[PDB]
Length: 147
Image 1 (cartoon, rainbow, N blue to C red):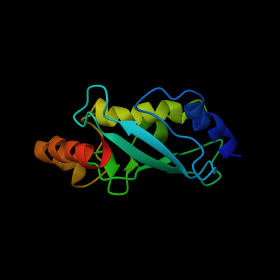
Image 2 (image 1 turned 120 degrees about the vertical axis):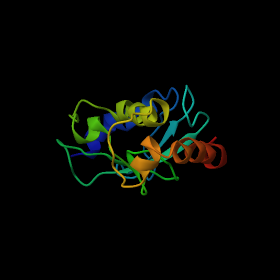
Image 3 (image 1 turned 90 degrees about the horizontal axis):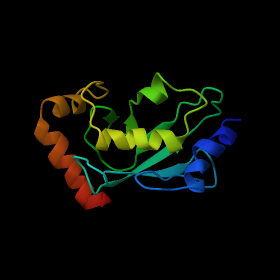
Image 4 (image 1 turned 180 degrees about the horizontal axis):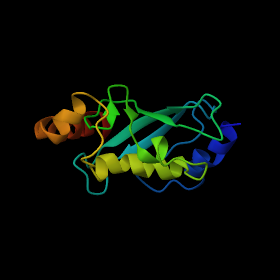
């Protein structure tokens, strides 16, 4: 019954797609869907229309959206499969958070850069340490693969 909750979370994104966030029925399955999360606002990777593919295995009520970057992206919360450590999806999730919600929050990892939660052994490091790795590269990917 998860997909039918995703009916809002995912499809509410399709009901009214503003900016830096859009998903919806891709395979027409609510477990294989494509969200375009963007640098566009004030972001280290501004310009970067990133790509998130999300899948669900019959989760609801508790629907943990494994929302994963299709592309490459340097940031402590994104490990090398695009899978994000996002509080509202790991700690603060409830059946009241649309992807219409989470997409902006994930956008906020490109937009808001949080210096807190380390998911990846290195990528968390290169973020809060190898300032080069985080900005230059993920913004370069922004230029190359996203934009």
